[PDB]
Amino acid sequence: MKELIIVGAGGHGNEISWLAKRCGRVVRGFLDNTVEKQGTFIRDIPVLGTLDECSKFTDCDFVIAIGSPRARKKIIEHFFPEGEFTFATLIDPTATIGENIHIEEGTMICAGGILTVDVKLGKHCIVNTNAVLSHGVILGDYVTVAPNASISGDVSLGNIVEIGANATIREKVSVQDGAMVGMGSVVIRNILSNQVVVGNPAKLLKVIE
Amino acid sequence: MKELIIVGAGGHGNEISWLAKRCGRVVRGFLDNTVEKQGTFIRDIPVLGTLDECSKFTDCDFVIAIGSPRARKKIIEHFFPEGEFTFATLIDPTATIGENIHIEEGTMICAGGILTVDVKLGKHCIVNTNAVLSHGVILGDYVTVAPNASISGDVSLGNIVEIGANATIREKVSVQDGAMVGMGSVVIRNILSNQVVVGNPAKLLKVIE
Amino acid sequence: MKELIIVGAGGHGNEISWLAKRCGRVVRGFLDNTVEKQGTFIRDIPVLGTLDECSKFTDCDFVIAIGSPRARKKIIEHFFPEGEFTFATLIDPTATIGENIHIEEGTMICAGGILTVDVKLGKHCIVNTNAVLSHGVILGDYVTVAPNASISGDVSLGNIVEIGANATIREKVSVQDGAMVGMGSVVIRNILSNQVVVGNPAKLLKVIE
Ligand code: NA
Ligand code: NA
Ligand code: NA
Ligand code: NA
Ligand code: NA
Ligand code: NA
Ligand code: NA
Ligand code: NA
């Protein structure tokens, strides 16, 4: 397979370099805009330069290993014009991927994640450690599902949605584009665009836009 | 082994047909009373007819793949007189079944479920995806444990109990017959018969009967 | 390897005898101070005597299979003077141990636990069933992490901390020595020494000392 460039050398990039190694991929290096990270390494993998160096690595697959949905969308739209680059899809060997699962490119399915049946993910999604997506779940593009999230049957998550760690979503709930569910939330009602909800049961905290 | 008939062609039946395939079982088909589902399929497995056709398949094992505890009890008592039918016990290959685990027939233990030591389940139980039953847990008949439920040591769940997704039950709690714990609940007190409790900490919402 | 002595023949000792068997270890027996447990067994493994018999088994590895952090510290300081005894480190075969994970002796990592990258544990820790410790997590000595706990990146847990079942800790939170997080808590703020916090979001309940 192509060597991999990981965009983002933070905590998620750290864990995605681990995922890539477990997937048998050779990581060429990271791109990252942080001044303090130039000339640094994670486990023998160098930070190669800033994101505008991506054009020097068109021979590589990319992945955008940054948790923020809006960060991944911003980076793809600025640095990765349609058709110019290829993206990896990384699925941990300990993830369970069942039947009629469709995953678009750039997606990361991490250790212990479970996608059962009839699940559809858009591009550049994250399903983090030990999260569960049950029957009929649909994710748009740039969705982040944090560790231990519990997403019941027939849930729909719009584009640039973030589901926080160990949150629980009732079956048949819809979450509109850009919303965010706080860690630990218990979501029993539909969520509107750009809403942040928190708590048990989840209630509106604020709007992100 | 015998071919399997799955009663219920809904979301749970979808996931239990997946479980059966992962268990190496041949699924003859589903029985389901929904008019709109007659002549339909899930992943090449047909809906054969309504539940009163069960008598045409006594050569098959059955499983009642319906989440509602009371639905499974109703169906067994009406359609499955004692001794006339055999029931499968389906344990996902990725479930962990430890030592001195006793599971009665009709039970479904799904992907990533963990039953550690000295756990006892009655007939027609569900332990859904990634749920954990720790030391000394006892379940009656027709218990449903939803995905990611966290059932601590020495918990007793009566007949026709339902524990919702990603709920947490304190060690040594007893839950009487027919009760239901909402998704995400934090249960730190005993629960009486037919009570619905929700929240953190769990409190009485209403009675189911 | 050396035969193992398990200190504590309660619920945790039950599950740790299971862990030891899954790890290929021969358990010589338990030590336990309970009068009613003298002459008893768990799955063919005898309670050998009280903790003051430890000096008769210096040929064995020990593990202190008691959930209470303060119980493990008390027992080590009274019965196990520095250098006189050796301690096992038990890691379930179904635990995922990633890269740059450092675990000190006496630690138990149970079934389905996940430690991703750059995680450090002190002595006599417990990571119970299906718990997740993400990038950069640090635990002191005698930390207990209960089943299904969700500990996000860069969390620091002091000595003798207990994190209850299915609790969730926000990234970069620090928990000072001796604190306890109730089961199911949603921890979004730093915790001070000896504080007990509960709820969603977690709030101070009381002080343990
Ligand atoms: Na699309
Ligand atoms: Na798991
Ligand atoms: Na779309
Ligand atoms: Na019984
Ligand atoms: Na009974
Ligand atoms: Na959980
Ligand atoms: Na230390
Ligand atoms: Na120290």
Image (cartoon, coloured by chain):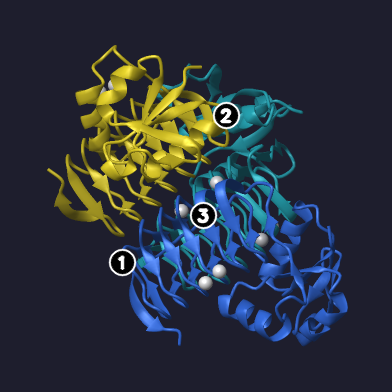
Chain colours: A cyan, B blue, C yellow
Mark 3 or mark 1, which is nearer to you?
A: 3
Q: Which residue is mark 1?
A: B189
- Label 1: chain letter: B
Whether residue A9 sits left or right of residue C59 in the image: it is: right
Mark 3 or 1, nearer chain start: 3
- Mark 1 vs ligand 6: CB under 8 Å? no
Residue type, label 2 = Ser
Crowding at dot 1, Cα within 10 Å, few <14 / some 14-19 / many 20+, comes out as: some
Residue type, label 1 = Arg
Residue type, label 3 = Val
- Residue B74 lies, in percent from the top left, at 63, 83
State how far apart marks 2 and 3 are (Cα).
Answer: 39 Å
Q: Which residue is mark 3?
A: B119
State how far apart marks 1 and 2 are (Cα).
Answer: 44 Å
At mark 2, the secondary structure is helix
State how far apart marks 3 and 1 are (Cα).
Answer: 21 Å
Crowding at dot 3, Cα within 10 Å, few <14 / some 14-19 / many 20+, comes out as: many
Residue A197 visible to the viewer: yes
Figure quadrant of the C terminus of chain C: top left
Name which residue lies at 18% across and 46% down: C195
Name which residue lies at 40% across and 14% down: C59
- Residue B112 lies, in percent from the top left, at 60, 49
Name which residue lies at 79% across and 86% down: B52
Is disc 1 in the same subunit as disc 2? Answer: no
Q: Quadrant of residue A95?
A: top right
- Mark 2 vs ligand 2: CB under 8 Å? no
In the rendered image, the residue lying farthest to the left is: C209
- Label 3: chain letter: B
Mark 2 or mark 3, which is nearer to you?
A: 3
Whether residue B174 sits left or right of residue C19 in the image: it is: left
At mark 1, the secondary structure is loop
Q: Which residue is mark 2?
A: A17
